[PDB]
Length: 4
Length: 247
Image (cartoon, rainbow over all chains, first blue to last red):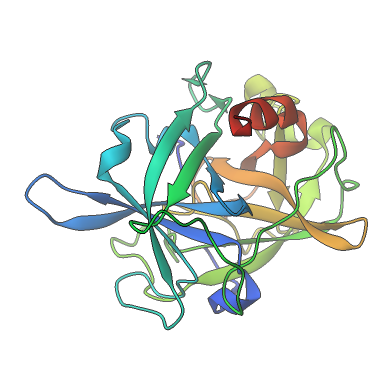
């Protein structure tokens, strides 16, 4: 996951 | 936030701390946001997409700590939770990663400026700072990408805006970064946003006032070489913001  | 320094809400008084009520009543931190007018907080769609019920969320302003009370903090319900209808996620990219929260107290009030609470300016349409400009980011996100806890005290750090030409190199992110995003990082790659900083502000000086230039969105790892933070580019979303902030 790249989501922050 | 990786690296940087602990701060208090007085140094980032537009920072909004967003929490979700859990069925059965535990409350946990979701994301950051920024107060752009008394009744409105801006954040990232991906924070909410899994749970779009406005009812579950609580927004705090004037709050310097994650899981304890700050003197002068103010608590709000979410009157309106506005996610971007064209939000999507690709392999890395999150597109149109922008959200609005209309806030109001149980008493029916919106935010009132104080020592610990202030709005942040929006930039003018397509007005960004030059690449190489130093900006600041703030949040309660992890201090190390491998941690399992969030820091209890607000943090912030300084990063530099990176050119699209640089960020789109194949050994950075390639086409995953669009013109509706901004990249930012430390030149030596020692400080960065990280998990839990999403929705938070990227703030730069523009026409002599602090301005919301980006919203913490995504990235590969935290503080890794050639992998900068990616931010939603606020100056390209003004019509969306204006339209969704009208009556």
